[PDB]
Image (cartoon, rainbow over all chains, first blue to last red; front, side, top):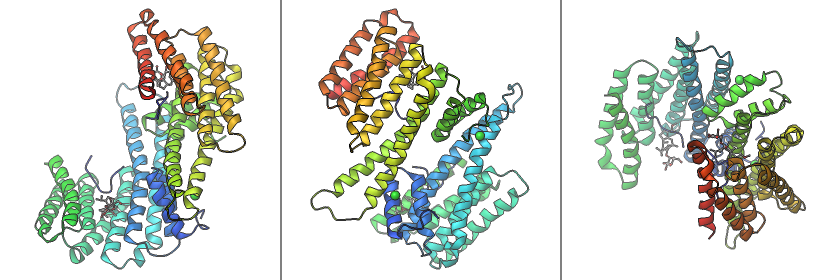
Length: 9
Length: 9
Length: 236
Length: 236
Ligand SMILES: COC[C@H]1CC[C@@H]2/C1=C\[C@@]1(C)CCC(C(C)C)=C1[C@@H](O[C@H]1O[C@H](CO)[C@@H](O)[C@H](O)[C@H]1O)[C@H](O)[C@@H]2C
Ligand SMILES: COC[C@H]1CC[C@@H]2/C1=C\[C@@]1(C)CCC(C(C)C)=C1[C@@H](O[C@H]1O[C@H](CO)[C@@H](O)[C@H](O)[C@H]1O)[C@H](O)[C@@H]2C
Ligand SMILES: [Cl-]
Ligand SMILES: [Cl-]
């Protein structure tokens, strides 16, 4: 739901 | 290059 | 095999879950287990088998093409020597791809094709045999490349002969076989004119049979017809 | 391990090829081999380690969420009994995901964290430790869920303390740590107000430090700042 880093490519 | 069937999803 | 203890119906159920989850290696392993139960596959089950392995080999083929392009560039004039690693890793991916193709061909030979009597099953499996020999041919470079190509051609040709006798020109299996055999001609067999002729004739004969179809069948057939048209536009 | 016979430099080279080929399981295996050589990792190498495992676990997490949603629906009133298969397959994917998280945590504990003295390495690894305990927490339901959550919180907190003392507010590692710790608060720890406060303070303190940066550093920091803003917009 929320954005995290790294993300999926 | 050319299209075949099935393809990748 | 590792799926030997799982019920056939449970393997099919899990193959469907794996598809929803985009877990194509699992999907393929479940479908391999289902085939190895020894019973014929239904139309839906054949489709699951095809989708699962196409997604697996598709990732391998895409990776192989990336690595082969890097390897080709490394062998150009002025390119700095970087050691054996690109070749090694291309070979690793290649060997894995070949193993998947061999697995599919093995399921077809033991014993899906020999038990397939209806045109819809037999053409489907012979097309698959052509496709996976075609993927082997894409990476072949040794004394057996010609035999691999001829194995792909032979499977496609038997499928073509049956499909023309037993299926209408709009049948989606017949259309997809023709599409892929045409790609074989263009990309593998160095026969672009045959590829173009096959795609054109297939498209035109399907066009002329659309009037016989329901709305849903029409949508199914015209989808594949558009792929034929796309290739013709690319090739001419 | 299976990479024990391959040179460190060759493992790094192949990890880069695997990334280009979108072969993330291979990439992760090469990077695990590189870590197991026992030397510290450079900044670029840490980034490769992070990207490889994030892509692997990301596929597993997405699959787990699909399967868990199907399983939850199956347990609703009026849903037909379909047997143990959905639970079994969710458990299979879960166990695989846990194995990847345990592998990452094992590399961090043996011995990346203990040898990491510079803030850029130590914060990076402690953030990773928080992240992979967070992924374990997402699937946990037993007597150890609270301890898993506290392990994620403890790793993130140590990373936060170091980052605030040793890094500028625009440092991308500091920003990404804050972003992910805020997601932990919102999604894992049932602390949306803490999540929002952390994201806001982080964003504002970074804004105030952008004037010190080059154009390239500015682009790097503002990218992550936008992710903070996106979460704030979602959460408020
Ligand atoms: C051995 O070579 C198999 C291919 C020959 C043509 C094509 C082949 C493969 C697949 C299974 C995947 C792509 C498509 C459709 C979307 C073109 C199908 C199938 O389509 C069936 O299965 C797919 C997937 O479940 C569904 O989306 C369709 O609704 C269904 O009709 C279609 O009827 C024939 C079997
Ligand atoms: C342990 O948590 C690691 C994350 C903390 C924040 C972020 C983290 C992970 C990665 C490696 C992947 C996403 C990004 C960028 C694109 C946001 C980076 C990295 O960015 C570096 O590496 C990526 C990938 O090679 C490059 O695209 C960037 O140009 C490079 O600066 C950036 O400096 C910090 C390290
Ligand atoms: Cl290799
Ligand atoms: Cl299972």
